[PDB]
Image (cartoon, rainbow, N blue to C red; front, side):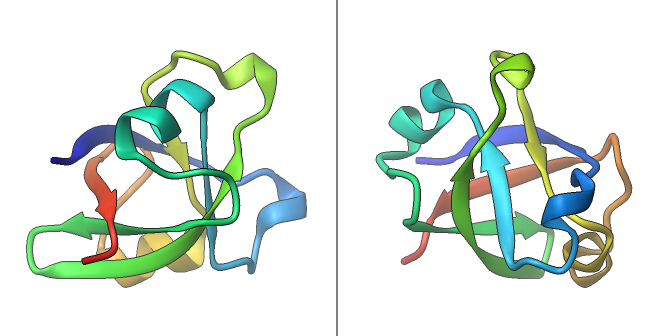
Length: 88
């Protein structure tokens, strides 16, 4: 089904992009590859974002990096948990 991930801040290069960063393990769990799309959900809010690969230092942290604009759309703060799933 879905994965639950902790929201972390976007690195400066990614601010303003409609993307999220997740590690390879998480992409495999979701059934997606880099460049595919996922839906990020919080209660009755949702955003669709393109999947870009997390940097190696972020591996296994259980996080998704998303910028302050996508966080605003979802009503979440850094440190909140979100549901991530394929677009369907």
